[PDB]
Structure formats: structure tokens, C-alpha cells
Image (cartoon, rainbow, N blue to C red):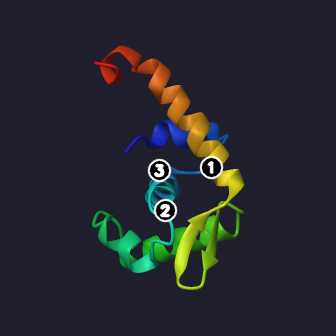
Amino acid sequence: SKVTYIIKASNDVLNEKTATILITIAKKDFITAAEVREVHPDLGNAVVNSNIGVLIKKGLVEKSGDGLIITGEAQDIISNAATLYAQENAPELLK
């Protein structure tokens, strides 16, 4: 997971943890907190919940009923980030 690009496009508001949780939510619309927790065994279950909350208080994620979905702000960081990465790895990606 390419969190350095994310932390970069976020002007360093994001750390390695809030960045990795952001990608998971970005990747699956209406994903739940319980599934975000399961794909990050590395992290504490209450750590994931905290950092999801830190992402809602920043205007990057919002809750839709039971599910989690990323804001337009968040998708600017994601598209910036992936374009950065893609250009630094282009000949490796394009084969």
C-alpha cells in the first residue's frame, strides 16, 4: 500500500495509518468499519475505529447509514497520489 504518495498529496495531514485506511474505503463504496478492521490485522481494532473517526472529522470520509464512503476532498488526494506514483513507475506498470 502506497501511503507515502498519499501522505504527500495530503500535505502531511495524514500519517501512515490514516492513509492506509483511506485507500481501503476509496476502493470499496459503502464498505463497513468491520471490514476495514479485518483487512488491517496489523492494527488494533480500536486503532482502526479511532483513525476512521479522525478521517470523518477531517472531511475525507463520511458515513452513509452503516457504510463508509470518501468525500470529494479525499478523492483529490487519491487521484493526485496515484498520478504521482504512476509517473514514477510508468515503465514497470505499462508492460
Residue 84, position as x, y percentages in the image: 54, 27
Secondary element type, mark 2:
helix
Q: From the viewer's perspective, is the residue at label 3 or at label 2 nearer?
A: 2
Disc 1 target residue: 75
Comparing 15 with 40, the one in front is 40
Of labels 3 and 1, the one closer to you: 1
On screen, residue 57 above or below 5: below
Answer whether labels 1 and 2 touch (C-beta < 8 Å).
no
Q: Earlier in the sequence, mark 3 or mark 1?
A: 3
Amino acid type assigned to the residue bearing label 3 in the image = Glu
Secondary structure, mark 1, is helix
Q: Position of residue 18 (x, y in %)?
A: 52, 58
Q: Is residue 95 left or right of residue 90?
A: left
Residue 69 drawn at (x, y percent): 57, 67
Residue 29 is marked as none
What residue appears at the point 45 percent right and 77 percent down from the top-left corner?
A: 33
Numbered label attached to residue 16: 3
Q: Which residue is mark 2?
A: 25
**In the rendered view, would you say 80 is above or below 3?**
above
Quadrant of the rendering where the N terminus is positioned? top left
Estimate the spatial distance between the alpha carbons at disc 3 and disc 1, rounded to whole Å. 17 Å
